Every structure is written in C-alpha cells, then in structure tokens.
Image (cartoon, rainbow over all chains, first blue to last red; front, side, top):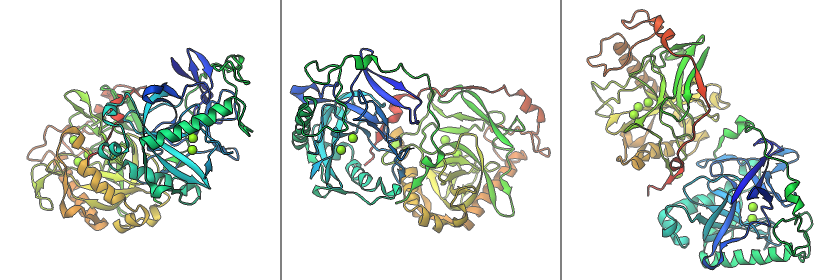
Length: 275
Length: 283
Ligand SMILES: [Mg+2]
Ligand SMILES: [Mg+2]
Ligand SMILES: [Mg+2]
Ligand SMILES: [Mg+2]
Ligand SMILES: [Mg+2]
C-alpha cells in the first residue's frame, strides 16, 4: 500500500512529500515500479501537481529518497500563474517513476512527464495506475520535453479510451488547451512562448510506449551506476538490493509526518493573466 | 464595518453566513445600502460565490435577515459543475442588495418576467473574494441573460480597490484589459446548467454587453422594484422575508431580529464529494 508523508507546512520552503510503502519512506524516483501491469502496459504515475493548483511541485533528483518539493528560484517559491481561460495546471501533472530522459534534440534530465486527464483531482505524492493514450513533444531550449497523455484506469471513461483519437472524442478541446497552455504558461514569468515539435500534434499510444520504454532503459542504466554522468542525482533506494546505492537505513532517516496546516499563498497568485 | 457570522461548516446543509455590522447581523438583502457613494455610482456588492468555486451559495430570500445558504436540489447540496474550459464560476459572483428582478411584470428588454432575486453581479478583478464579503464596486456594463426563460441581468463590475480599477470605466475597457472574458461569460451562462439536465440559456441582444449607462438604468429599475417590495406594496412578494433592522419607515422593521440570530459556530470546511471535480465537455 502506498501512502504519503508530508514534512513541513504546504506552500513553504520546508515542504517535502515522501511516498511510503507500508509505512516506510521509499524513493519516488527509483523505488516505485514503472509498471503496475507490464503485460497490459499499465503504468504507475507519481502525481506532483493536482489539477487547478499553482505551486510548482516536483520530485527532486538531488535529495535522498527524492521527495516532492516546491521549485524555487533564487530562494523564492515558484508558482505557475493563471493564464486565461485556464486556472493553474489543467491536468493532474506528474511523472513516471523509473524513467529518465538521459541528457548524455536531447533528453531533459528528468523522469518522463505525464498529463493525467481523468475527472478526479489527484493529490501530491499519489501513486495511481494509468494507461498511456499518446504523447506530445514540447521544446525547451533544444531539449525534448515529452508530455505523455494518460488516464487513470479507475476513471469512469477509462474503458472507452485507448488511443489519442479517443481524447478528441471524449475531451474535445483538451488537446488544443494543452497546446496553448504549454505554449503560454511561462509568459507571465517574463519568458517567451514555447514551441512544440510535430506542429503540436499528439502522437499515438504506440509511439508513446516506445518513448516511455526508452526512458525506462535509460533509468535502468542510471540506477545500475552505469550512466556516463549522474552528477546531482541521488540514487539512494530502499527496494533494489543489488544496486550500488541501496540503503534501507535511508527510509528510517526520514523525519516523522509534519504537524502543520497549509501556509497561506500570497493573494497575487489569484491573478488572471490575459496573454 | 461589515463582517461575517458563520454557522457551521462550509459545504454542509447547516452552513449559513450572516452579514454583520458592528458585530450584529443585518439583512444581506435589505439592510446593506445599494450605494456606497451614490453621486459617483459606487455600489455595495454582496459576494456569494468566490471565483473558481462550485457551491451555489445564495442570499436566502425566505429566511429572516437573508443569510447566505447553499442551494439544494431534492435536499442535496447544489454545486455548479465544471464546464470545460472553465473551473467553477469564472467571476466573483454575487448581488446588489436593495434590488429585485420583479417577477410580476414582463421586462421590455427581454419580454420575460424577472427571476425574483436581487440583480446579479459579476466582479472581474484579480483577487478572489469571500462569501459574505461586502465590497465596493463600479459598474462597467450589463448582459441580458434569460436564465430558464426569466430576465436575469448580469452586471459587469470591478472592485474599486483592484489595481486596474482606474483604467476601467466602461464596457469597452473590459475587452481591452480582459480580452476574451466577455465572450467566455456569454458561453458560461449559456451552458452552465447543461450538466444539471437543463437546456442551454440564451441572451437578448445576441449576448451584447451593453454599456455603463445602460447598466445604471437597469440597476435603477431593480432598485425601484425593491423599494416597492420593501414598502409592502408589491402585488406578490413571493413569500420573501422582508424583516430588516435599518429601514424604520418600512412595515417589517425590527432592530430585535438581529438579537435572535444564533452566535457564530464556525467549523472547518467540510469535504466535497469527488464528483464535483469532474470536467464536463459540452460539445
Ligand atoms: Mg517533470
Ligand atoms: Mg520533461
Ligand atoms: Mg436559482
Ligand atoms: Mg442571484
Ligand atoms: Mg439572478
């Protein structure tokens, strides 16, 4: 059973979320199997950011057991601003564990990103089981920043969704909103409009699976200690006994759950930008 | 100074929010002056529903001092559903006090009776409001919604404290600083009850947002209708509770009514059923 352990108050620099397996912290990057059901391509997704929230939460590669923390720049907590007509993130946003876009266009140096499109709003550190529907390629300064489009297998519509064309049928306009969102979401931060490969097209399930599998193989090399360069990445794990960086003690070293209410978010984050 | 008195937990059947002045409840419908500054047309808006929320909180016409209570259907709490690409209400949503959409006459602009409620207000500023807030707003324009066949004007307004307020003086300024918002507003009010199994709504004037001058004229009409109502002179007051604590020349004045309201019993927000998360794709 996967649960979460929160350290610190939400919306502060101290906030960290660890994933627990049967009460014990594990690495959110390395210890959660990519596949819930390999034969049927059911993936575990680690959720970082709930739909319609603003705080830019991410698995941190550099801290032991890779908790989810809020992104910072020069000491300041980072938020996505509201970009009309959107409110925060428009997907449950996260990543596949045991994947890595090896930067050694080029890998983006993180687990492959996942947009989960189902009805229910997720929680930070949730491990849910999803099926892949397709994939888009956002460009980020020469890096290929893939966005997998997926749905929770427990979603009421999941049986009716198998490939990318089904997203057009049951979620008309969501692909367009996705294109627009990733194009404009940094404009309020003083950055340019972003660009997609393939003229913004979403490639199909088959294509997505090939990319996901490649990033899993890269992670296999990484965790084995065999990548050409893993600088800045903590590979400590508590479930892979034959890896050089196995250390069960790392689980015990994590502090207990925080006793704290969410810190308030500055009211400026409410603002709707027309851009 | 206006404050709020909350009974119970938000998102429960027991929840009520009374507006207080001097720590004592007043009628949210009748006792809050329409104008904060009459000569400059600065209005008091009673906020019901914050932007990006779902619970259909409303001033309760039939309850003494007209607290804000969540609407219900078959006894179950009513939440407006998320209609793609929107999340809940896309404005801070509320009403002008001391107004009434007269249900006993056909309104000439729409050829329909009024919806029996205070005139509704869409406040477009950056900050998300709170339920029971009294804020001061300028009117910018107005849209002639027919909501389930009833005259249901929507005033477009902005909080006078918004950073952009000085630059927003008439409806054309809304399109300049909030491009796409008026078009989205038209869509929202057309489609928002389709997930409830109701028809699409429609607008008069093909959804045109009429200007500030037009808005002031309609606001005046609805204030005049309320003046008749509160005097006990409506042909049919629809069981509305006209009890008030600030209008001595009215038959239903009673300073005592305030003392009869229970004390605050504020509880943490109750959870909302996960179904309310759902995003509906209407076409
Ligand atoms: Mg990522
Ligand atoms: Mg990426
Ligand atoms: Mg109603
Ligand atoms: Mg109303
Ligand atoms: Mg109305």
